[PDB]
Image 1 (cartoon, rainbow, N blue to C red):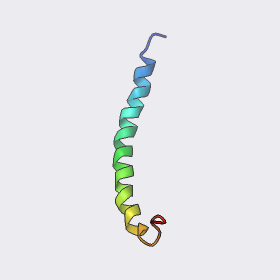
Image 2 (image 1 turned 90 degrees about the vertical axis):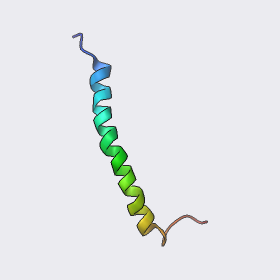
Image 3 (image 1 turned 180 degrees about the horizontal axis):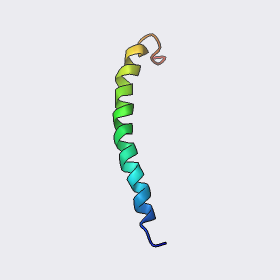
Image 4 (image 1 turned 180 degrees about the vertical axis):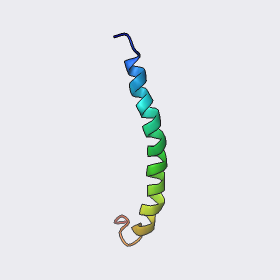
Length: 42
Protein backbone atom coordinates (compact mmCIF):
# COMPACT_ATOMS: atom_id res chain seq x y z
CA UNK A 1 0.00 0.00 0.00
CA UNK A 2 1.62 3.20 1.25
CA UNK A 3 4.90 1.92 2.69
CA UNK A 4 8.35 3.42 1.97
CA UNK A 5 9.39 0.96 -0.73
CA UNK A 6 12.48 2.95 -1.66
CA UNK A 7 13.27 2.86 2.06
CA UNK A 8 12.94 -0.87 2.55
CA UNK A 9 15.15 -1.35 -0.49
CA UNK A 10 17.78 1.18 0.49
CA UNK A 11 17.66 -0.60 3.84
CA UNK A 12 18.80 -3.91 2.44
CA UNK A 13 21.47 -1.79 0.77
CA UNK A 14 22.87 -0.43 4.04
CA UNK A 15 23.21 -3.92 5.50
CA UNK A 16 24.58 -5.34 2.27
CA UNK A 17 26.96 -2.44 1.76
CA UNK A 18 28.28 -2.87 5.28
CA UNK A 19 29.21 -6.53 4.97
CA UNK A 20 30.17 -5.99 1.33
CA UNK A 21 32.56 -3.16 2.17
CA UNK A 22 34.30 -5.40 4.70
CA UNK A 23 34.20 -8.25 2.20
CA UNK A 24 35.82 -6.50 -0.75
CA UNK A 25 38.34 -5.09 1.71
CA UNK A 26 39.20 -8.44 3.26
CA UNK A 27 39.52 -9.63 -0.35
CA UNK A 28 42.11 -7.06 -1.43
CA UNK A 29 44.69 -8.25 1.09
CA UNK A 30 43.87 -11.89 0.36
CA UNK A 31 44.00 -11.34 -3.39
CA UNK A 32 46.99 -9.00 -3.22
CA UNK A 33 48.62 -11.81 -1.25
CA UNK A 34 48.27 -14.67 -3.72
CA UNK A 35 48.62 -11.95 -6.35
CA UNK A 36 52.39 -11.50 -6.88
CA UNK A 37 52.68 -14.69 -9.01
CA UNK A 38 49.87 -13.25 -11.13
CA UNK A 39 49.67 -9.46 -10.84
CA UNK A 40 49.32 -7.43 -14.04
CA UNK A 41 51.53 -7.30 -17.13
CA UNK A 42 53.37 -4.41 -15.45
